[PDB]
Amino acid sequence: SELLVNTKSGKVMGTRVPVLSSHISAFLGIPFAEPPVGNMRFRRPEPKKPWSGVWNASTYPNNCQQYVDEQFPGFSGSEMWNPNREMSEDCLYLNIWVPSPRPKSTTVMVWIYGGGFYSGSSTLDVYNGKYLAYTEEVVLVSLSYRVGAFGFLALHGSQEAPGNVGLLDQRMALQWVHDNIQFFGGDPKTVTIFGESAGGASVGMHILSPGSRDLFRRAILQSGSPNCPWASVSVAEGRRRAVELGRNLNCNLNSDEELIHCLREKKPQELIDVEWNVLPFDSIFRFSFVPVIDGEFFPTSLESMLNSGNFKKTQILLGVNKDEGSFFLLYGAPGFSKDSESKISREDFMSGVKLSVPHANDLGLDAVTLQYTDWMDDNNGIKNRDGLDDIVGDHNVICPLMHFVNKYTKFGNGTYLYFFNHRASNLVWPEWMGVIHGYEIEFVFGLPLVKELNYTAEEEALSRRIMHYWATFAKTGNPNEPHSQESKWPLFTTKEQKFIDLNTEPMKVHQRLRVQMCVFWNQFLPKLLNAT
Amino acid sequence: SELLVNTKSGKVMGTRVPVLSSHISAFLGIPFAEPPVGNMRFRRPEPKKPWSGVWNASTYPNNCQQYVDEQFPGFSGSEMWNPNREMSEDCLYLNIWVPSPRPKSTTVMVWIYGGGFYSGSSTLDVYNGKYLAYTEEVVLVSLSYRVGAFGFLALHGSQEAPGNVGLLDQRMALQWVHDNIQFFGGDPKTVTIFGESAGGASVGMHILSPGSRDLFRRAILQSGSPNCPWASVSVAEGRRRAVELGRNLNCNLNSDEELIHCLREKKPQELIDVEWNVLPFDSIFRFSFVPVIDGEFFPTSLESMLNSGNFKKTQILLGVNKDEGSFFLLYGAPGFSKDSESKISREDFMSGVKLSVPHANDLGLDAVTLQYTDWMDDNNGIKNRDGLDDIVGDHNVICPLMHFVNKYTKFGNGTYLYFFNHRASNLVWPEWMGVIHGYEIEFVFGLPLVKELNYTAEEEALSRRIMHYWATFAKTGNPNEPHSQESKWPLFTTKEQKFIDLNTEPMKVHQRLRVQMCVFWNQFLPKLLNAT
């Protein structure tokens, strides 16, 4: 039977699903690790024990325990990102969409969801792999991993909460794909991992971490890189936040054992209710429990790894969205509102700058303000709004990714860069937010191909192009069709630094994506803060 | 006799001179102080002793002892600024151009020449007051003052070389105009002092210094202000340079008396030959002996005087030239040449930046470089050239003058600002130099009205407009004709900050003259250098 598969962990029973008036197979909720509950909380994941009988993989699994956004009850715009299944600590499962008839040895794509390392689910509607698996004929896999304190509590030096266990979760899911995808028709020597936001940062971390390098062939990073100021902390800051977490729940703090044990007796929602109280500064775009430079998963500091070429050399395709920051300003900066043009005063502008660059002294805050202010029109509400929007995106997503791509390209075997600047016609968020963080995802998964979702004809065409780029790159290491007649996505080189825009207009090639600012955020400011 | 005048110092005999096919009276070389020679060198000036008989004032006086530019032998471009008379320490004289028939009580204009406080003469062809006195019917006076070590050697604490004696020279010339101009037809209660470069800086210093405030009514400042980074030094740096001067001439350095005496036995050219060896840094646009904040001429620091409103309140008219820096780059920065387009490499660019901001640490040099570089075209030879040109002008002339005008306007009784951006059609300097430092002078003195000099018709028209503005402002405190139909030069206010361009095109009003950079040079950089 096409829906029955015999893996090294036991038999699995999938289900048939309709897609664009056709059908493909889907194996939902396959376990890849033992449930990380009770004594296992905060602990490294263990391989799932083989099982007899047939595993029913016809329905989505639960979502990991996480913080749930309630800033806009009912609003589809924000609820489409919330967990759509019962949350549970028993969350380590993966999903597979296989073409029909079943392939013999085709290209594999493993998706890693984003969510600031504090949220995310593989089961969201925007992550339905059926459209992509169907249209491009690839085996699509979406894994899951623990988030928040459950996957990133770090008390370096102990084995009960070593840290980075959330990344080990992803690595284990990849280990399973490596050992079993052949039974689903996938080629294990041709797996491409791709993700967005924290997922894009995760993908870059597997490229850097020695223990993950051999588990995949290529990588796609969307709006996120391993060296983002929010994606990781020192073992010291990790320890500091873990303890403060314990202090908010009145736990015995005399020893790691004392603290960990107390945290293991707590109900999931009890740790989530106080999770945001441990941040060191009043800030925007910063999260409590994230990966930590421990000397294990990451041998040394990330910057020295990037300079010494200490990372997997292969091809990578990555890019960013035009307005990466508007989302975090809406939820956390004074002056912004979902229902207004949000014109910002000088007052709120400088107030927002303090929230965006939390680790900066006054001299630094002044440097940023000078770099993003037009003194010929300093009280222009729309210029201060977009200025604040650029700052948040540049510092948190764009400038950090450009530093990675430039460091990587010096040792890699091929880089392809894009700038996504098309605002979907059906977006429910206000206009001032522009091309929002995470909204290029829907084009990657092909949602525009389904009429009932209401996209335009040009938006459907754009989705097929992107899907064909991502898929063609996954298979060959180049997003372009060998002998095509279409426009060529030029390769990004240390010298030219070419990149393309991704929208519904005739492709255009550009150079040096936001260099002026990237030099400010990657060369000048760091130096300023270190001297002063 | 129209050419005979009886002043409080004695009788004076002038000469008749032709101008634009007419005639006016000229009294050249009238003494206003005793010759500052021998024991008087470096000493404060003394009033000239009255004389019997008639003083022959029909020929120009000598020029003060000074450094002479020989970088381009024969080249009119640079020699038109060199002394055109025998140099001598006996140099304190003034020149007066009086309309014919002699006025009864008309507006007076006293010109103070520029030259970095190390050069200058009242007798240059470009400073011939006859055209202006004739065309606008005003009494025109040009004074002289000691420059270089002769007028600025400063050994605070002693009375033999107190410092600022060069400024006291100007003040004395003004004292004479105040006590005697009435006998030449001038109104002593309506004297306007105006100058360019160091002369513009001098004018601003008389506005600040308590002892000079009552000697004039209004002031015009061209391309120079009292707070320019090159116009003054601390008593300590003054003392340091005076001593180093003595060390270059092998003088006994055990005491001020020892040093001063040794410097007084030296021939003029001996001090001039080593004058440039005392600068503290390898630099561009910096001079050895300049005014010093001594607590006498200047009560306190200049910045505190400007903030407390401690200065003469009146009307002022001032502005700058488009390309104030090209002249100092030509003579002192690697890469620039009089006979080439001078395209600058990245190498020379950063090299020039080090020479332009001599007192800056590496962090500061990097701030400037980032502020003036276009990272999308960083190896563009023409962009690095103009970038270096803007830096020198902004830091040395434009940003400092904007700080003054903004501080002054808060307490003054009327400010008028201009931006001169017309390059004369007969300039002998290369094109890359643009609207050069000091070339607005020729329009102020009316040289374009004389056919044989070869200006265009629009350039002659521009000269009459400027002459009428300067003269109409000198008489009324407003450059505009009461009920004219022409375009109005709007008043500069703290709020709007309006200013006009000065060229051969239909007047246009603008706002916030180079604010972006002025905020960098007046607010950010100072702060950066002080924190680091």
Image (cartoon, coloured by chain):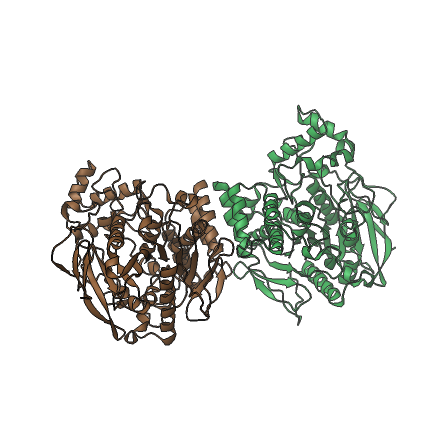
Chain colours: A green, B brown
- Position of A48 with respect to B108 (left or right) is right
Question: Does residue A103 appear in this view?
Answer: no
Above or below — where is B375 with respect to B271? below
Question: Does residue B151 appear in this view?
Answer: yes
The residue drawn where x is 15% and y is 45% is B39
Q: Position of residue B268 (x, y in %)?
A: 17, 51
Q: How many marks?
A: 0
Q: Position of residue B33 (x, y in %)?
A: 19, 51
The residue drawn where x is 69% and y is 49% is A330
Residue at far front of view = B104
Residue B456 sits in which quadrant?
Answer: bottom left
Residue toward you, B49 or A39: B49
The residue drawn where x is 75% and y is 47% is A143
Above or below — where is B373 with respect to B447? above
Residue toward you, B221 or B216: B216
Residue toward you, A42 or B490: B490
Q: Position of residue A470 (x, y in %)?
A: 69, 59
Q: Position of residue B402 (x, y in %)?
A: 43, 54
- Position of B462 with respect to B238 (left or right) is right
State the quadrant of the N terminus of chain A: bottom right
Residue toward you, A477 or B227: B227
